[PDB]
Structure formats: structure tokens, C-alpha cells
Image (tube, each protein chain N blue to C red):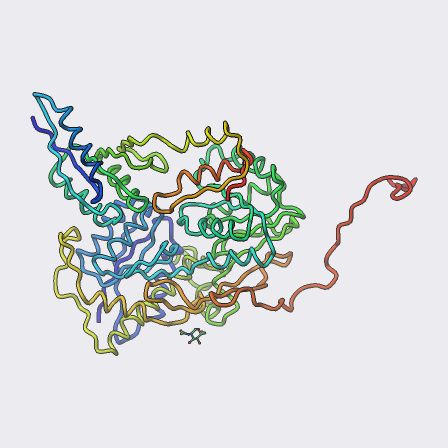
Length: 152
Length: 404
């Protein structure tokens, strides 16, 4: 009763995969297991991800574990939304509600707002990389008016 | 004589499509002609975008004219960079240099950054919409820390239309904390008309407020509702109706029947649509130069499934890129030209101040020259009722015994 799963891993993900490989071992039972198809791909390229997602759809997996990037994120969300494929990933949470998506990464933006309150900050600098995204920076700039912040 | 191209259109973009049809007729010669394949699809559904793009790559086109959303721009750009397929679009330019992309929309980022510097602003609001990329937001924020600006950036895009009256009143309750009187609206021409009607409801459009619409269709959206409140309104117009070329187009435009051409019986045209008419002229002259250059571009056979691994790029797409990126014509958006990346270059955005007499061509910019127009001759001397304030305190200001 072997069950197949999609495995989308970036190239440099050595420990992420090292922990993934350990994950399946500690959880496989005597009546079923997991048969992942691992595609080491450059996750930023939307075409590579799109071509890789279908490389798993034709193989007929029952769920896909992977990652995504600010550029390729909207590629996976609407793809799993129409094909009813279930996608599980630790990449950053979807900006909005996108169905058939499982985000292990807990919402970091909600916790950061509470930290700045206890420290009683008023003016500070916010450093962000447009690569990782800015969904968290957007949140602190939105609440910058209600809570009196002068973000540089 | 037949050239195949792919067309990706939002289903709620009819004038944007009506302008495309008129362009085929005005640039159809007897030497050759272009042939479209239209798929009305959802612009935000990148899966539909992927299904539409591969529908054209399997039919074997030479270039694709379409749009994209933030949720799909990366889908369009990534396929064109690998399959060497040229893409022409009037949507927002890509956040970076992407090959085989011919962005018809010019970069507004340079305009706003010095329209701010013209009025001498150092603190303002910035209500943006992520539907057209966070490119503009990073620009103002990067320049905010350099000039020690104090900006308030609000992701006004993600708001529900059912609780729109209690949240908009709440936003201005938040913007009232700093008594903000200088705002920049960075929504599409649709959500702008929603904010406009809600600024009127709370009366935040009188003497004192000053807004800047950050899109290339100032005269497109409805401006008559906030024109007389007393608040100065600035913006940007790309379709300079003063040019005789546009008027030549607008005359033939205003007489067209509306059942056959939706959204075309009026005197103005949306900047999204005006760029589309100008897009055809680019593609027409692109291939006409491939002809005169004695260049053979026709496909050698079935392009196959787009998901072909490894992705084989047809070499002549390089020549199509070089053909499209070396076009140079004139249309409704003024001048038209492209770099080696496909970005708009050598253009002119008319800056318009909304006075009491309507949109006024006050200024304009360029990627080399910033704010350089002398004041329009039309105006009125001593039309400014200067507002003066004082305090009732005898005997400085006493109400006459017959003050009623």
C-alpha cells in the first residue's frame, strides 16, 4: 500500500532535505509508507516550478511537498486551487486565502506586532529584502499609522 | 502574408480590446497582415494564464500580446525567457530586466518621485494596490530614507467591498491622527473612483487636501466629482489629446458605432486601451523590418508541448526579440521605443493639475528631464479668493450691531 508524494526541493536545501529524509523514516508504518518523487529544482523560476508540478501530476501523486518563492508562489496556489491537488510546504504564508495549500510556517507577522508593543518603540529602522518578500513589512507599514511608528 | 500572434485579454477589459480591433485596420497594408487568436480568460488565475499561453505555443505563434496580474506576471515572464517567445503587454512593467518581454506601459516610478519633489513634499500618505506590483512602493520607501521623508504606506488593496463604509471611515480616522493633507493613490483607475466617492462622503476634499493619482489615466477616471471641492488634484495623462495624431484617431473613434465597438463612442480612451492600439503598430513594423532585412522567421514545424523537457528554444525568437525591440513608431501614447530588455524608453508623461476648469496640461516629465513646462496661457488673473482667518475679540474684530 505504498503512497506517492511530490517532493519539490531547491538545490541548496541540504539540511531541509536531510530532515525530510529523516521525517519519512520515523513515521512509516507496517501497512503503508510514502514514495516521494524528488525534483531538485531552482524554485524561483516560475517555468521550472510549473513544469515540475506537472512532472508530478502525470506521475499521479496524492499530495506535493515543496517550497516556493515570491515569484513562483502565485503559480502553485492557483494551480492547486483548480486541479484540487493538495500542496504542503514550509515556505512563507500565502498573502490571502488560497485553498488546497498547507503552510507549516506559522504566521510570523502576527507575533512581531506584539513584540514592538512590549518594548515600547516609536522610531526605528526596518530592513527587508524584496527576495524573501515584504508581506511582513507591509503589515508593519499598515499598522504604522494606528500605533504611531516612524519606520525608516 | 499571414503572421500568427496570441492574445490574452481580461474578460472585463472590453475597451482595452475594442482599441485592438481598430489598430488592425489602420495598420493593415497590402504587403501582409497580422492574425490574432483570442482567449478571454481570468487574468489573476495563473493556471488559466499558463493554459492560455501553452494554447498559443502549441498552435505555433511568433509573439503574444496580453496582460498579467501580480498573481501571474511571473508566469508570463518565465515562459517567454525560456521558450524565446516575445511578449507584448500594456500592464505594469516587470520588476526587473526580463528578455522577450515588450512592456508597452512606461515606468511611472520616476514621475511620482519628482512630482513629489516639485510640490516640495516631505510627509504624505501612500495608499497602494498590490494588483500592479510592489515596484512603486519600494521606490518611495527607498527614497523615503534618503531624503528623510516621513511616509505612511497602507496596503489599501486588500479590503472587502461589503464592509467598505466602516473601514474607509476608519482609514481616514487613522490618517486623521497625523492630520495628513497630502495623499498619493496608487490603485487602478477602478479602485480610485471608489476612494474618490468615499473622500466626498466625509468631506475630505475641501481647501487644504491635495491628492496625486498615480496612474497613467488622469482624464480616464471620473474627476468631476472632486473638482470643485477646493482641493488640488494632480495626476498623469499619457494620451495627450492635444496631439493631432490622437485627434485624427479620436475623430474616427468618436463616430464608430458602440454596439460593434464597446466603450468607443466617447471622446476619451483609457490609457490601457490607447497603448493597445499603439501595440499593433509596433508588431506590424516589427515584421515589416524583418521583411526588408531579408530575414526568414517562419517556424520550422510543430512547436510541441510547452512542457517539453529540456525546453528547446527556437532560435528565430532571438530575431523576433531583436525585431520587436528595434521597432520605433508614433501613436496615441506619444513616442514609442524599447531597450534591449523591452522596457518603455524615450517617452513623455503629461502632468495634469485638476483646476476649476478641468484637467490642465500644467507640466510633463521625461526620463532625462523632470518638470519642464511653462504655465499654460489659459488661466485667470485674481481668481483666487484668498481665505483669511481671525478671532472675535473686541475691538480687533467686532460683529456690527446689525451683523445679521
